[PDB]
Length: 46
Ligand SMILES: [Zn+2]
Image (cartoon, rainbow, N blue to C red; front, side, top):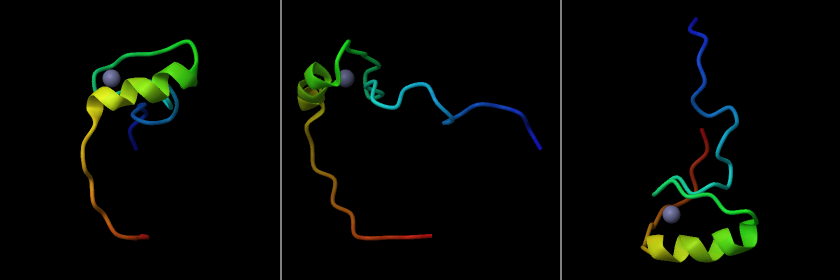
């Protein structure tokens, strides 16, 4: 059992692609545009 932090809080909305944060999610939503692209994927649980 290792005690580390990978995805237990930090950058929930903050852009991870480039690593840019914004005061409000509003402006952030538009920022995602720069990272425009396709990503097909069906429903999968498990
Ligand atoms: Zn970005």
